[PDB]
Length: 303
Length: 323
Ligand code: NI
Image (cartoon, rainbow over all chains, first blue to last red; front, side, top):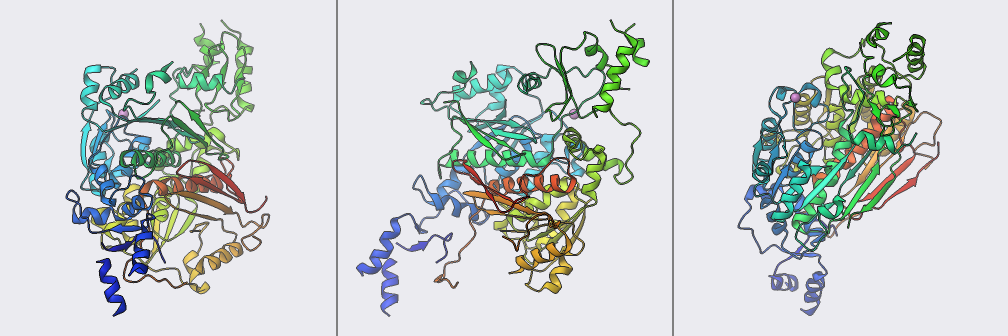
């Protein structure tokens, strides 16, 4: 037993005693450290590398700070490397999630997108650089993802999500987590329910963002189905339904980087808490809504 | 006005703009407007309807004029290039949507290219702010830092990639920023901020905005008050984040003034961090800095500090001074 006062905090066990005089009282400080302030470095991981433990170090101290699940700090990092996350959009919120997940040591990224990089994507889509223009988005994403973290394995699917139940189970494949917005959404949710895969939603704009509920899909939780069934409101409703009278005028969606990174950050944090259990995740059954104008927020229960 | 959608409510009412936003709302429009507006990108139009009346068509066009909803094809930017207007397009749409300072959309972006932001420290909070600012078309970035990239910086400091290990942070930073946005000028100072005002006024230089963390800090603040330079504070951890207040330093708001050893032993005590907390913090900052510089929309954080738990998502404001 070797007292590692958790490298987060500023200020043999038999070794410190003998080195000190050079017993219950030191025994007293060591033990009372069981108030979750002490490490037992005596454990090394049989999965993670020398490089990885170094690279993942500063967040590993963070898992160990809360240690909700009572594990050695690498076990948490282990639960990320064992994870497989599928992302069904690869511009907007999609590249920021991919980015921050790869940086965090997520095991696998399954990326799905049928688009290609345009110069107008560069202001907000963080995985694509000026020289990536003209590439297919998923190819650029993987290229970029591995330059950041070479231990992340990336599976890329150059296609859109069609409402084909046979194709989606292939696209979902053996995922451990799913990230998506807002029938194809519904077919996936269903796939997710069948394979017991946690699913997190999200969506919004520069004025206000939300990071939708988590569905654990372990059983013992409500699941997607249960949720399935001048007014500032009516034009809200009409817009999400895409009914626009634009005609031959070409109108584009107004988006910029700040709003995406905020929800992408809320999303990645919540996903990391779920996978690892280093701390409890708020967003199970809740929707967090935050104005980016006046910073008022609110919660929504789904179950 | 290519920022605005023309929305069709179920009952048939129309709203020109996605998020009024002070978008015009036409209630119970004549049958003729849905085909009218639908053809207004390009006298001319009355032709196409060949049920509607000629004078009734001009008033409609008349109206859309004083409502500031109609496009100005005659305006070209002498500041922005062909490439920038492309790359900045969608955020340009976002400015055109709220349009608080009543300007042509290009003008707002111009106000960004003309800006110079100095960032003190390229740690976690530091790297994300530089990035999103560069992406957003900030004119010039002044990076101040004496460190070099470590393998442990790679999990949270986003401007640094694996091949960047061992390099100077400000130089690795500049290489990365320029891969993302070649239009941003980057001035780099491989040094830490000493509490010498003689150097600090040199490091600040002709900055137009300052970002720093929650001492040198107080001199930078004094330099800022003296030169009328906005300063935004920030800070927190993986558990709760805070951003602001912003100090306008215009003389019509209260100023910054108005408001040991460790028994460490042989263990190395480190900063506990992961990326998610930083992105939220830089995005709140960047949005607030962009709104302040350009004025396309009003910034909340002037004189206020916003605090958000990342555990249970309770937030709270703290006033630091009144406008
Ligand atoms: Ni395309």
